[PDB]
Amino acid sequence: NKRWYFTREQLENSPSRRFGVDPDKELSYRQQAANLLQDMGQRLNVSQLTINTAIVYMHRFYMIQSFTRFPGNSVAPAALFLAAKVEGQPKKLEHVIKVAHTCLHPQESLPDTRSEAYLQQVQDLVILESIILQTLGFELTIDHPHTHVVKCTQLVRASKDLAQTSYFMATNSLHLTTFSLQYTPPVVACVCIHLACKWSNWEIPVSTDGKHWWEYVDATVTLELLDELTHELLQILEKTPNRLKRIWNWR
Amino acid sequence: SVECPFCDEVSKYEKLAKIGQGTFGEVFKARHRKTGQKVALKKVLMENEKEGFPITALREIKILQLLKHENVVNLIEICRTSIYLVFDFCEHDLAGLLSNVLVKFTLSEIKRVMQMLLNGLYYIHRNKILHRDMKAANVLITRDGVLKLADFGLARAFSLAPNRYTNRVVTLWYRPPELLLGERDYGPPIDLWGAGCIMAEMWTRSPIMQGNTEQHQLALISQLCGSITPEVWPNVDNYELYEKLELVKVKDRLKAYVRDPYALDLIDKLLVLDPAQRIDSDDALNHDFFWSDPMPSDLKG
Ligand SMILES: CN1CC[C@H](c2c(O)cc(O)c3c(=O)cc(-c4ccccc4Cl)oc23)[C@H](O)C1
């Protein structure tokens, strides 16, 4: 219930840290694994939801296991394979392997599907899915910040544009941060609206009571946090080449 | 060689007896090595599994983790070494009790059994889930006399957008008319049909409609429930299977075994042909059957 939420001190003392990996290198390895998930995900034609679920699996997996023993390039395909089954869009084992291969070795050649080499890398993916399941203690039901985004974008009568920017922030928080390991989905959703608003220069009208739009979403959320979190999210977005461009008003 | 904080090895339990044989796998009674707590261990089947961990087992596990209720069986955890589902142990199943000729049911105990069962259906349906495998063998009872709905292997979530749900569900004998007519757009009412059959079963000791094929079942249903005409089931003819086999009175056949009139009445509102006219969990729990003497009493027989 609080099993998969971690303090900043626990994020510091990660399994990858115990094996040498620096704090900034680790953040990097997660961003890379997310990118790999998004890439395979779009080619396998699964939904952003299936991918987000995969990304959270990956995130939680590396709070127990280390990047030095379990390479993201091995874990991500298996995580995606599992998430697609959990989320209703099963993809075939051979299909996920072909797509993982073309993403990781664009120039290499699809191995003979009859070789003892290929047969083995199929077994390796089935072994990893089992390791992921056991590591997550079979807890595969994931709540995403998106679920709660529609709930509080009607609460600000926001345009279709403000809403689509909020989902973009939501999806990007999963790729770029570790909020999914620190804050409940409802809180992360507020952070996403709050920043989509700052970015779009949409100002929210004070409620009839005097209270603010987010109070009707999570009782724990305070402006002191929303500003600290939207600032952290914004900084990482600025470091990520071409991302802000996608939501940038060119007019 | 790998860390596993949240999936304990099943060796923590000590097997005592293989209590369940069939095509559902292997069910073991076991005992926690430290506390003596009894559990049911149900191994996850891997016959011809070429797509990794079985998607159907994920579904079942997803549903069990969601359903938390006094009358739904309780998944404690999941274990390894191969993979085991671990439940709180339930000593009896309703099929085994219904067959032991030495076991006897007072009417106030029958009332309580049906009450716990109907309360379990009310719960799972509120949580947007269909059981889809109603039958005596899937109703369990604990040593302390609490009834548990079990085996969610065919279970599935539902909702309300024309639904595209699968047809070959429910064992033939407890399968409801809709499914036999080839229905694909259904919901909770299919489980209540099963509850109806199980309820009658509490008096007859034997499943009441023992069909051989889908058409001999439908036949047997007619020789108990009347014919299936648009006069009884509006727009039933809208389905492309009313073709065969056609044919043109439930309280009568059950008079002998079932004496209580309120009991007979409820059985008749559950074994209704039109799903839209079939009684639901809520209204069934409110039926005078549960609110007249003898009142429902705890189980000790
Ligand atoms: C078809 N079927 C019925 C349910 C059964 C099952 C479950 O799904 C879950 C459980 O916790 C139990 C249990 O504790 C005891 C028994 C049991 C009890 C007495 C006789 C025979 C049996 Cl199989 O069965 C259980 C298994 O899925 C196979």
Image: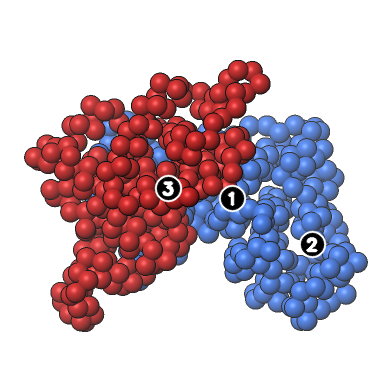
Chain colours: A red, B blue
Q: Determine which quarter of the picture holds residue B275.
A: bottom right
Instruction: Please count the marks in the image.
Output: 3
Circles 2 and 3 on the same subunit: no
Q: Name the residue under label 2.
A: B273
For numbered disc 2, what is the local secondary structure?
loop
Identify the residue at horizontal 12%, vertical 41% (top origin): A21
Horizontal relation, residue B232 to residue A18: left or right: right
Q: Mark 3 CB in 8 Å range of ligand 1? A: no
| Quadrant of the rendering where the N terminus of chain A is positioned | top left
Q: Name the residue under label 3.
A: A248
**Residue type beneath disc 2:** Leu
**Residue type beneath disc 3:** Trp
> Considering depth in this image, is A50 or B111 the residue closer to the camera?
A50
**Residue type beneath disc 1:** Ile
Give coordinates of residue A117: x percent, y percent.
Answer: 15, 74
Q: Mark 2 lies on which chain?
A: B
Identify the residue at horizontal 13%, vertical 48% (top origin): A68
For numbered disc 1, what is the local secondary structure?
strand
Judged from this view, the residue extending furthest toward the left is A20
Q: Are marks 2 and 1 in contact (CB under 8 Å)?
A: no
Identify the residue at horizontal 32%, vertical 33% (top origin): A232
Q: Name the residue under label 1.
A: B129
Q: How crowded is mark 2: few (under 14 residues within 10 Å), some or many (20 or more)?
A: many
